[PDB]
Length: 285
Length: 285
Ligand SMILES: CCCCCCCCCCCCCCCC(=O)O
Ligand SMILES: CCCCCCCCCCCCCCCC(=O)O
Ligand SMILES: [Fe+3]
Ligand SMILES: [Fe+3]
Ligand SMILES: [Mn+2]
Ligand SMILES: [Mn+2]
Ligand SMILES: [Mn+3]
Ligand SMILES: [Mn+3]
Image 1 (cartoon, rainbow over the protein chains, first blue to last red):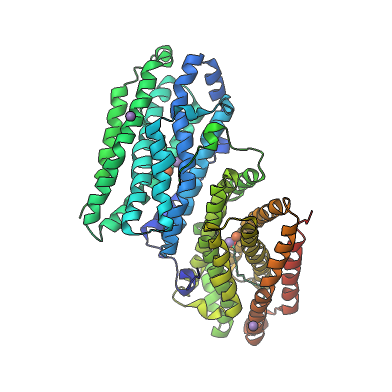
Image 2 (cartoon, chains in turn blue, green):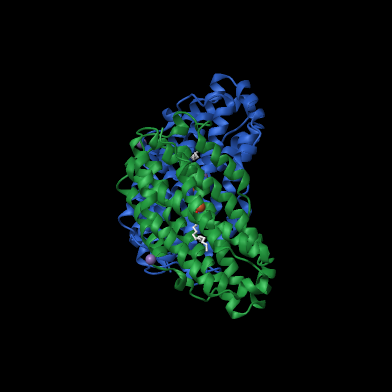
């Protein structure tokens, strides 16, 4: 369907737009390249482990590799919907969002290749709760935007993607990686990647907050929808956390070997804290 | 619609895929930031010009600003279509393609802001032929991909976007900018941007060649479709070139002032040469 005109012909970019400012920060802070990460010591760490210790790390990597790939594919309908609404600065920013996710997919896949598990199918560590979030609910909410870009639909898409997948699960997985392997001295290349990912993710979450708040600013009754959509997904968030916890409690050899009191009760509470504080970053008024 | 699984969980990125290699080159060669270009001398050059000389440069900038904005919006359906086909490496590459176009929009809009014409509506320099390409035919061909991702549809989309808009018009506009202003010593910041754009554009055109050739490799009869779709748009390509030429011939004060024998017959022949050589980069066999 035709373009009726172009903002940068009739006028200019809105230089003061919050998403233009976020785009500018993304360019400045987004230079890192996964191809430059030295994974040679990760290969050695992984080979040094027993099979039982090897396993310990794979469920979390399985969750991230699928998650990064899902969000790379599934952000495209948001870019389309805001493009069709004429929100040029949002779209400029989203090009950095999408390119970030591509690098995130690349990073975890390089690590798998380097440590020797590229040929292993890690889908076995996706339980029903994970699938409900990543194989179903996320693509459903985003793809809806192609035929329904109502405020309700945009709120739901940003809530599932930015507040739950990124702002609750991703943030907690970054924390979990540091709490376990940074402590152990293991996988320095992976943890360099996690640090870069965590920096990118901050901008993604801020886009989600901006998006949800500007819709809530129009009609405070959308605040109730945001809360409702957060709570709808919580059972799957915690059901996946519990599954990963149960796997950690059953395979403890990496913990013993490296003297890690991995506090699964603390990890759980970090997740609950992440979820509650995303809710508090949306002001009803 | 659900994900059935993820390539980077079951396996890895196809590291030898041509579009993964193009993505890798795009990251290495795509660091430039329009925000770092010094436009202070462009502001002075522009203010130094007479109104009659001022006008000379605006039609070409008008064509580029709209063109960059159109392609930023209109590449999204190609990313979607290849994503839904599972072409993960194409999608990774396309994130760099989209982010490039965002920077291109930003670059021309910064120049307009800096030289003092941000408030001027440059739509007056889009004639009917230009509109047919950029306001209509381009969005029609790309948006079709949301409901029709047949080889015919993908060939047509790549032909309009990558071979005509980028590989014929953009390439010729880069040449035109150098032939006129690089000669004059004018607008150094703009020409720094043009150089960066021309480097990015090379990767975009190569994606289009890859895309069209891999479909032609399946069924040589698609070669005829490629040629047919190139010829369908030629009248609008040359009709826009003629319009810009006629405007250049009527407002010649910048040429006289700066002693430029602007060879409009040469510019025209560069366009014809661009078009014919894009055709020859697709092998029927
Ligand atoms: C054992 C403690 C549980 C901690 C929670 C771990 C969750 C793993 C994260 C996997 C999904 C990652 C989503 C990526 C989204 C993005 O990159 O924007
Ligand atoms: C007077 C000689 C005519 C030369 C032809 C000039 C055409 C101007 C170009 C405007 C469209 C630019 C399209 C940008 C596409 C992209 O950035 O991928
Ligand atoms: Fe993210
Ligand atoms: Fe381009
Ligand atoms: Mn359960
Ligand atoms: Mn005509
Ligand atoms: Mn990510
Ligand atoms: Mn461009």
